[PDB]
Image (spheres, coloured by chain):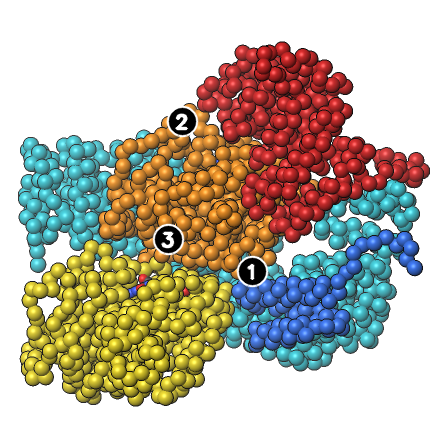
Chain colours: A red, B cyan, C orange, D blue, E yellow
Amino acid sequence: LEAFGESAETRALLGRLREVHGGGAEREVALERFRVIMDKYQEQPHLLDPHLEWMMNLLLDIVQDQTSPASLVHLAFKFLYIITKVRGYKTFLRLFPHEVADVEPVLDLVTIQNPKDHEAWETRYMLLLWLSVTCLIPFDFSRLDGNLLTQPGQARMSIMDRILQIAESYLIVSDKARDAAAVLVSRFITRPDVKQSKMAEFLDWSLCNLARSSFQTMQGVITMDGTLQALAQIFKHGKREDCLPYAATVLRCLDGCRLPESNQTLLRKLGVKLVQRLGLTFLKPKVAAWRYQRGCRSL
Amino acid sequence: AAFQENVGRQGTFPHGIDILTTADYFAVGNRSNCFLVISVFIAGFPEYTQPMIDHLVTMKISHWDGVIRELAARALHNLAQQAPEFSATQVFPRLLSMTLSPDLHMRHGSILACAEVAYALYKLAAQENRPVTDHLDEQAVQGLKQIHQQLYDRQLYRGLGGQLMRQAVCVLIEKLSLSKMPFRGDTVIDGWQWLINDTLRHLHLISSHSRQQMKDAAVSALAALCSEYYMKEPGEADPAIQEELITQYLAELRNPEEMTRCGFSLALGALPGFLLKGRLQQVLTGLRAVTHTSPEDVSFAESRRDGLKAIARICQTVGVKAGAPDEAVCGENVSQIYCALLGCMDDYTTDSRGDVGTWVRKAAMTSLMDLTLLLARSQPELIEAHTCERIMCCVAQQASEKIDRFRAHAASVFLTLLHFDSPPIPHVPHRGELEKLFPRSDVASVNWSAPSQAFPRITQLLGLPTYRYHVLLGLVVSLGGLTESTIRHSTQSLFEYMKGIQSDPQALGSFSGTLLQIFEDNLLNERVSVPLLKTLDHVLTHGCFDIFTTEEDHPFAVKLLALCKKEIKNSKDIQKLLSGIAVFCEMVQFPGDVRRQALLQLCLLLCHRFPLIRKTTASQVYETLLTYSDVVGADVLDEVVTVLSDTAWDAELAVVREQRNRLCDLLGVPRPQLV
Amino acid sequence: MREIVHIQAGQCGNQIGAKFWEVISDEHGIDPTGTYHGDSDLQLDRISVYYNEATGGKYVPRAILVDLEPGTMDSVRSGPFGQIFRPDNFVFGQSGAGNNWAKGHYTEGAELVDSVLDVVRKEAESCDCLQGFQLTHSLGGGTGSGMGTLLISKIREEYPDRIMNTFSVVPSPKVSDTVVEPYNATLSVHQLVENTDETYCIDNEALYDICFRTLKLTTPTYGDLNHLVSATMSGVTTCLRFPGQLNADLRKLAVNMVPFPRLHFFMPGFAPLTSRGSQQYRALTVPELTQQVFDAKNMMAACDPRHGRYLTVAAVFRGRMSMKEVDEQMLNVQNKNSSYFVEWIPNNVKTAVCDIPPRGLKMAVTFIGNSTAIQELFKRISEQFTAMFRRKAFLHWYTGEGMDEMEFTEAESNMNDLVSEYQQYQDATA
Amino acid sequence: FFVATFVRERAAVEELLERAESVERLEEAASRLQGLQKLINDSVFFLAAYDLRQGQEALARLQAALAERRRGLQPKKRFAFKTRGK
Amino acid sequence: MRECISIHVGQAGVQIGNACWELYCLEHGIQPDGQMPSDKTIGGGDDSFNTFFSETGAGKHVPRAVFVDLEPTVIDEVRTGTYRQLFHPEQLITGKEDAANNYARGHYTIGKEIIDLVLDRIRKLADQCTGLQGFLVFHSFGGGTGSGFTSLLMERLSVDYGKKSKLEFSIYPAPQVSTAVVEPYNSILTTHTTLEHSDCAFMVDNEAIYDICRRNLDIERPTYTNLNRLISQIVSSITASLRFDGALNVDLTEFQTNLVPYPRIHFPLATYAPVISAEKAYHEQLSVAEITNACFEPANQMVKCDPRHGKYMACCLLYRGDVVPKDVNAAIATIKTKRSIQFVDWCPTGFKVGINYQPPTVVPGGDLAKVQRAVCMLSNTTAIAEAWARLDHKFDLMYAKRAFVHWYVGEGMEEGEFSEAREDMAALEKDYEEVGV
Ligand SMILES: Nc1nc2c(ncn2[C@@H]2O[C@H](COP(=O)(O)OP(=O)(O)OP(=O)(O)O)[C@@H](O)[C@H]2O)c(=O)[nH]1
Ligand SMILES: Nc1nc2c(ncn2[C@@H]2O[C@H](COP(=O)(O)OP(=O)(O)OP(=O)(O)O)[C@@H](O)[C@H]2O)c(=O)[nH]1
Ligand SMILES: [Mg+2]
Ligand SMILES: [Mg+2]
């Protein structure tokens, strides 16, 4: 192809989600048509860049409406996940809203989600990613919280503690949402205020989970995988002088998990990945002095 | 990609731009191009001639796959004209030492490389009015004259591994004989003759999967060796060598083994014209017997195939000549060939596998396609009128069978023999109508293999009285098949065609007669009888012969009833019985004495030997009684239907004979006797 | 031979694969967690044929989810039973194969087959004695066809003596609207006849006609197609998942249902026909089930058994019933409808009974036939293939990826010779 | 005869490995494995599938045993920088 | 004193051998563990029952059987059954891969890997015997393993123990109990392979047993459990001479001399009578003349043939119960004067009478009743050849179309073997027809 030709059809299909959400007779056909139309650009997702901004505005206005039922908001979350897997989350979530006012609403949505609802997992996944986008704000969570002692007795939970609890609860699920949590770990525990109040705690919990997990049970393996992914994200998107004071302790727990003898190929990869990020924490980045004199950027 | 990066970032690769513009993301996609085209272009420079050939000779030629070995051999052949000295001085001796290695694949690859190098050197020397011995020194001539001999010394030709050595030796002999070598009058030629003869005398010992190949590889090698060494003078041959070969091959066409027969048949169709001059009638009489079917050669279907293939092959070698029965195709031998070719058409063999005859009926269709055409390019007068009409009728008949594959070949042959205008055919029944029905422009886009795009067009040939019978026979044998799509498309075309003749009486008085002649032509054949009854039943159920039902005792039904009596009488299979009971209950509609005779026949069949046949006949009688009207009078139909629905046709015979007699008495029909 | 490895390529193959696993888990009592909770010892007598024992008495699947893109891989992992599989059994890429057989058989597939043959040898290593293979893919899609046929060839080249069985899903213009699906289908056949040993024909046109005309559906969806494909899979493999003497292993089933090397295409059938959210309280008798299972309407392929001759027939009756009545009904069906059965392979109709009926049905019946009428499923493909190949349409997609017209010629010739052999064997001794 | 000679060579290789205490012991043992592989790959044009599978399994087991023996007799030292080699 | 060595290979072969051993010990009083209270001599063995049982210095009476299976299924049942303490772990051989109904896969592939193991067990067991008579092999033509591994073992024994008899008890295929369409090919193959390696083999038409179970025993769906209980009784009645103090067929050579005149014609016809159900046990007692007249009825015959059409070459009868020689002689004379029994012109026309005063025995809870007297008539009749005739009808219709032939070609087996076996069967049929003149 060369450009997007199915513009009116896609627009009509996106403007039809408000009359095909109750009964599933016209809900499955719409999803099938959308998937068939989007799969044609699986190899050329760059040809969708100029259409993925207006499609996200139409999809966001439906989920942001308070009068949008659960079945209607979940339908808009499936299309968003489809667009993400088609184009790419790195290039799609970057355009999502990132203002300050979008910090409290989004989080609230994440609180009204049932992890035991496989019929709407796409809602629990994409949502998490959107949260990770609202941690790129240059303010603190204490300023947004304001006064927490507004109610008698029962105090209000800060946004930082809520995000930490949500991340700790979803890094140990089997579904695709654990992965999303790893995105929040690289956007929440790497913040300036969150690191100062959620780095010792998050690193003591991860070590405990690594120490009391087996690679011979289904759950323990999931918890170990989630912890390894979180540690890798922390060591990658984190600083070297904030993460270096912990790289010896982590290396030890990793070596103790006797992974090079497991028959779990994905655990070994995560262990190797975590072994190279910890190692690069012990040495300062250097710059190729040999550039600007051996070839251009392109050919 | 690595080469492109190195050429773009360093620019130190010799001929980087050239090897980068020719070999790219698109041109490199094809492996054949990379191994034959791009290879020569890249080796054209002196910086890639030695290493490329070295790698091809010390790796690719010794691969573990025959396809890769053949590709490397072809690459070396193509790269043998950019480096004759290196191919005749460092690579050729390099291969002579590897041809004797213990490894089988290595020996095969080395033999192929040597043959290719010899062929390339011969082709290069031919373009300079010089012999091939100049490049191939005495050393090369010796080793090449020791490949076949040494192999036989180690009984290396035995076994599956020996089959590949046999094929390699055959290819080498073919290449050496095509390159014109100075091996005339040496024991090497006798040894080669022996090996070719053994390969064909033992084809039944060759894997069926890799058989047809080893036989088309031994006949080809025989055609080059007998055209470069069996030649005493221009246009002649050694009398002694011509008397031993033909006598040996014509005495092997009557072997008891079928594979040997086929091998000798193709070994007799590759003989040069200088070696058939003086004894062509003998070979002709030999293959004629090889393509015939005797009481003992009923299952020899593959023999006739290769016989017909060889027969036409010798007609195209010797050409046509006036006054020369022993040397070429004159008018004294043109009639016998046509008779032998049209004797194989009526060849349907339903052996354990199925219509093995389709293979013999296919080959014949080709032999004529190469005969009538050949004469059309020289002596078109020999193409008789009756013989050509019979050929055109047989082709039209074969172009309507139930086998899509063979029905696509017949249509292609017909189109190749009808459109032919270079020059066109002298006698083609209705050549103007055929041209109008088959526009040359809208012919290349017709999928004859698909029934949908084949039946609607072939059915239009019924309008020609000449091909009417032969097309109706094909449509009949194709309608009574078993495939759903085929029968559906045949019935649709038949109904869309009979609409224009149903109203016309004379049209329904010519087609009906033709169909009844096909019933008298094919009665008790068991190939056309079964499908012809089903077609008649379908035509009667559709309601086509309605204008004749008004007349009483019409000759058509009068003879159809006698034919059905002669056919259905004395049977066993249930399909024929059911098909016969259907035709009878459909023909009952015709009034007159024919109605009474059909009712009597139905009452007789009612008490068949099998209870299932009895129940089927009872049901069909009840159906044809409740459907038609005026078939039973005197208000006796109520009692008839009651005694038919009450009588249990699944009981014994002594209990149902009384009910049959009562029904006959109630219908006014004589009661058959019991002896 | 007591462990079978499961594989699934393409979106449809993975979906058909995930449905069959869920069905056999619900029938065996294995909840999504992995613990046994059924109510019959027979469910555990043959549980090691598809599952593996793990600490805590858990039953881990033995499947391998394979794809070239991540959509279907995330859809199955998040399904109701998604947690059951192994996190390192999901092997996929990012770009797909774009409905091109070449892209899925020579580029992305040729690159991911390395990792695919890593998990495959991981499952074969945890098998006392491998018995065979059971792949689930489609012949229409590019990735599902190309890379999946590339995995059959690699397994046949690696494992010398191992049975190969597949569940090919033939596409249909009524379901999809893609033009290059005839080419993606023909080539696949050219591989199966020369690679796979057993192959079930599940035509999409037959499913569409059964869902639109029989079940009464205005817009049959892919959810209805997977509801008919999973039931057929559960019915045809009921002998390998429970005790039995007829076809307990794959080698016996092949020897009994494969009279010739090239001829091994079996059209399956299941009765009574049902749909999602439908409970039939009426329990059909044994004669009614035997008469309905042989009906062309209950066939998963677009071929009429009456317009052909049978070669090998295998029937299974699941439900509490009597064996004498079933045997008498089978004998009566063989005697009455005797013209539809070749008389040159004596005892070519087998019948089996099981005491574990499917879920939601008290009486079920199955049919795995080897009639020559299946040739009709290929003739249709032939017409489309020839019509699209003679004018050269969308051919640059293949020739530009290493392929050439020689492969299409070869596949067309192989398929055409398979039709002629079927027609000849149908008229043996005519 | 092919199966007989294959079993004989396998038993010989096993006996040689069971008593391997030199690099020459293991190096000669790793040249009988090459010969066996070359023989088998040149005989798959007339052998059955079960025999080929058995030969492949035997070759894999022998290669694993040879690798274990090489790792045991020759324990590769851990990685260490070349700083202050002398 | 001499002792035999029995062998049971395959699913049908081992399942019948288990019931036979159960019935043998059931009659000898040998407890399930192996202790025989009736035996007063410990360590010494020289009685009639020692032909099929050895004795340890504790008392245990071990059988002389060789249970070999190519898959762990039937062997596990006997290993964790009731008589697992009766046999030793070494005598219970087991393999892995199954032949899956294929003579080639069992004779040139999965059978040439475990033959040596079975042969080493057949040598260790024989070393503990001062005298050996022969080998009683139990197999089946339907199972490919019973056609391949059994034939290989017989061929190897013909070379090893080249001076010992090899009596056989094959099982003939039937459609009501069958699970393979390739049972005629393997049957013809094993028949052609064993024709030149056996002395006397008794056939067991599964159709006859099914009919006897559905009519006499009054069973709606006879199962392999009921068939094994009815065939074990006949197997024991036939081998009753080799386990009791009798006077007929005491040795294996006696069988060949009294029932196998022509070396190639060694397929006698066996019959057993009476066969009354357990419900009709205490009803009526049939005399010797009552069970001798029913023996000739095709309903009781083991093979579905018509001996009345053909003639006989040899005949013998073995009784069990309170049978008097005078009554048996009178019944035989009456049957000869009534029925028109014809014998071959060059063959001796006499009946070998052999009475056994021991009463019959049946397993508790079985469908067979404890009859007061039973008889097993073995007569070599040419009508049995008809049983092979129909079998050839299943070999020409399929082999003509080259059906299921690739399974043997791809397993190392040649194609000419089928033609050779068919020619051998045709020659055997021609010899049978010539003997009828
Ligand atoms: N029955 C059924 N057919 C399906 C399903 N999904 C796809 N198909 C059919 O499969 C064909 C398309 O192949 P896909 O499975 O989408 O192909 P793939 O394996 O994903 O390959 P690429 O699309 O090239 O990446 C068409 O004929 C569809 O109708 C499904 O769930 N059920
Ligand atoms: N009478 C009787 N027949 C049996 C028995 N078991 C199997 N059969 C019959 O034997 C034939 C098949 O032989 P099996 O014993 O099952 O086969 P096998 O010898 O184990 O062979 P493979 O499994 O192929 O290696 C069929 O005709 C069965 O009906 C049994 O216990 N008794
Ligand atoms: Mg896809
Ligand atoms: Mg068995």
Quadrant in the picture for residue B77: bottom right
Q: What numbered label is drawn on residue C243? A: 3
Disc 3 residue lies near ligand 4 with CB under 8 A: no
Image: E346 above or below B334: below
Nearer the camera: disc 1 or disc 2: 1
**Residue C339, percent from left and from top:** 30, 50
Image: B264 above or below A263: below
The amino acid type of the residue labelled 1 equals Pro
Same chain assignment for discs 1 and 3: yes
Whichever of labels 1 and 3 marks the residue nearer the N terminus, that label is: 1
Label 1 to label 3, Cα distance in Å? 28 Å
**Residue D77, percent from left and from top:** 79, 59
Q: Is residue B62 left or right of residue A13?
A: right
Quadrant in the picture for residue C215: top left
| Residue bearing mark 1 | C160
* Residue under the image location 36 percent in, 34 percent down: C274
Quadrant in the picture for residue C100: top right
Crowding at dot 3, Cα within 10 Å, few <14 / some 14-19 / many 20+, comes out as some
Whichever of labels 1 and 2 marks the residue nearer the N terminus, that label is: 1
Crowding at dot 2, Cα within 10 Å, few <14 / some 14-19 / many 20+, comes out as some
* Residue under the image location 79 percent in, 42 percent down: A279
Label 1 to label 2, Cα distance in Å? 47 Å
Same chain assignment for discs 2 and 3: yes
The amino acid type of the residue labelled 2 equals Leu
| Residue bearing mark 2 | C217
